[PDB]
Length: 168
Ligand SMILES: Nc1nc2c(ncn2[C@@H]2O[C@H](COP(=O)(O)OP(=O)(O)NP(=O)(O)O)[C@@H](O)[C@H]2O)c(=O)[nH]1
Ligand SMILES: [Mg+2]
Image (tube, helix red, strand yellow):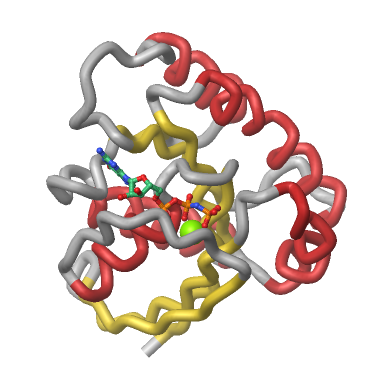
């Protein structure tokens, strides 16, 4: 059983914790309880293999930015999450990707672009915008809803596959 060190990143309130708690506990956290940092562990089957997911749920609040360097060193793949109704969180992705490449000293780091809250009406970030960003970064782009569970498994399983190829 291969362990995978996933890190969920993104601006405050985009749904990083809700996506994680949905994946591992199958329930939707309705209240906004801002994260500092929490670790989770979930065993799954992806492409006929048993793997353990080591998931770090990080803080979007800028006040805790001093924790980023340490978790970008140890993590192996990054779920970069924005909310489809938060233009700033989409723009923040550039800044996360840059800091990750800096700390990894590499232009090829496993990551997946996640546009969350797709259950909502009147998104301010259209799909075409996010596709072009992800294509330019050379990473997958998956639309999710932590509330309905749409795309949650797909987002985490795709990141596992990205880490799988980088190691091999
Ligand atoms: N409608 C909708 N609401 C969502 C979705 N995901 C999260 N939310 C809601 O948005 C709020 C923030 O979610 P949360 O997961 O705590 O965000 P976070 O990115 O972990 N915030 P922090 O960086 O402060 O921990 C909560 O009220 C939550 O219920 C989603 O897919 N759809
Ligand atoms: Mg959180």
